[PDB]
Amino acid sequence: RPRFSFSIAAREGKARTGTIEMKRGVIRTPAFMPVGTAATVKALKPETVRATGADIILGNTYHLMLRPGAERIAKLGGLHSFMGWDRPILTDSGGYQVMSLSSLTKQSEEGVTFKSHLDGSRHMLSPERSIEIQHLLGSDIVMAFDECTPYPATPSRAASSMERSMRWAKRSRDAFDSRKEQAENAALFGIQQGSVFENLRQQSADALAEIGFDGYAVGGLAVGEGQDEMFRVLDFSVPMLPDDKPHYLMGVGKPDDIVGAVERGIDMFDCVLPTRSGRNGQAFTWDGPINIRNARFSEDLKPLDSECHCAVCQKWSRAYIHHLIRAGEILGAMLMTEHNIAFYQQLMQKIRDSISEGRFSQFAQDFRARYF
Ligand SMILES: [Zn+2]
């Protein structure tokens, strides 16, 4: 019922479990958000995504602003009605994908100019245009527009990028607030930057806290630094953010990354891996990933995972999925993606339960032992 309310139900070390209540639904944390790139979670109907246990999905603003266009989606009734997902949706700012998939990017204090990677170039993206687009889509959780720092980054480089991001954070907050309908029904998350330098991370955290956000994302990670570095940065960075607000780690999704991140105080995750790997033939299991294409699964009657309770593993065998994937059949992608998303959701549930029972430490230890 409320616009945004985060409650921590239980804690264990830095890990915590709770719920985020929003107008469109409740989100159980730690949460994993499946990625909906072009207004669709790859090969899955919304009902199937919900069936796996997902409380919220992420919408890629970059893709949507190009096709079919934020203005058109708004005219059509908003992203929710368009794609058939009635629960909360978090949309990114679009900046990350602009710097990664756009042609001839142009950085400036006002924003970034670019060429669409498919057909001419729907072209200007600033803090306020980003917020406007997210409003047009009608997302529930809006991300502030920032400048991600590449890895590696020199201190001065990371500093200047972080400083710009904080100026943009303020501009994102102001833009969000001017739009009453948006400020009253949506939530705004700020993004901490600063690369791997704790002094920069600290400055970022403070600036962010001074502005004030509904949630805080730890940006600049999973960009080539490796798990060890990521974890080291999380160790000192997360404690810098407000404890009573959700902590969101953007673009982090390997099962072990998630477990280690939750141990360090992260509440939300998102990543394309489950859907992506599904199409590639990689299935996640409690005993590690397996590539279903390999010949040893040709006559394996066991389900993808014998402890998974998803619909796929309750009805089909590895042999069948192996056949579908090697035949390049669409159902192969459908089945693999459903199981993968379900596996992630089950992992999150086990994490939430273990924290609530004060045995998350043992769970993480046992998980790693079996998974590897
Ligand atoms: Zn399954």
Image (cartoon, helix red, strand yellow):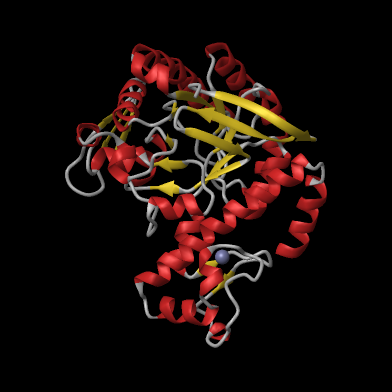
Q: Where residue 245 sits: x, y (%)?
A: 61, 24
Q: Where residue 9 sits: x, y (%)?
A: 71, 31
Query: Residue visible at 42% across and 72% down?
Result: 332
Q: Is residue 251 left or right of residue 116?
A: right
Name above or below for residue 183 compared with residue 345.
above
Q: Quadrant of residue 116?
A: top left
Query: Residue visible at 62% across and 54% down?
Result: 346
Query: Residue visible at 79% across and 43% down?
Result: 357
Q: Where residue 46 sits: x, y (%)?
A: 39, 50
Can you see residue 70?
yes
Name above or below for residue 183 compared with residue 91.
above
Q: Is residue 325 left or right of residue 318?
A: left
Name above or below for residue 364 compared with residue 146.
below
Query: Residue visible at 52% across and 86% down?
Result: 298
Q: Residue furthest left?
A: 120
Locate ligand 1 by image quadrant: bottom right
In this view, the residue in front, 326 or 166, is 326
Q: Is residue 273 left or right of residue 305?
A: left
